[PDB]
Length: 229
Ligand SMILES: [Zn+2]
Ligand SMILES: [Zn+2]
Picture (spheres, protein in one colour):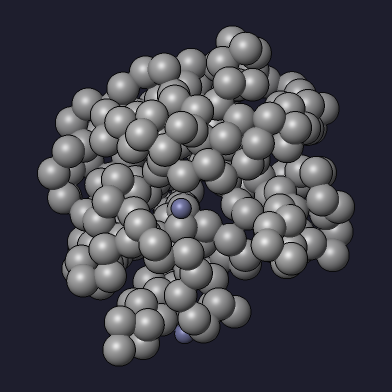
């Protein structure tokens, strides 16, 4: 799996998880440190569904160029998993390239309030914790508030791949990240809903860092509870 060792700042690498399923990894520089951020790419026939930008116009343009070079299939739809700039930043680049950008109404409202880029299309049917909707080759799930009140997770049933965005932490992260917008009280319950819905998941992608198995869910609850206390 690519780490910041192999990815310069402003560059994007793809990692093929299964037939028609990739993660995208971008090296982000923020507040003195650098870390890798993950998103997802899922093939849907002869088109691609993108989950999350690469954080910013420049990185997301690099993401599209890397997809064009490595995969050569068009990104026709994108979903942002919550409203923060790292997940919607670059939506304008996607839109200018002809990608239909999507987010829940909650994510769109919060992005607007924050002054962030706003996906054009609305994902209906995700307003209540435990709501799930099918979206092409993935299921979108609103597990409840966690890293943010609007955070979605994404499951690829064909590959048993679960992408958690920033609701799921990598094992090397043993303290809470940015939780300014988090619901610490609900986060463990929201993780339980993820566990209850996708107990068959084989490949779990955290928002940042190395993928793992379903124990990343317990890891995240451990870290969240330790921060709560
Ligand atoms: Zn966030
Ligand atoms: Zn752990």
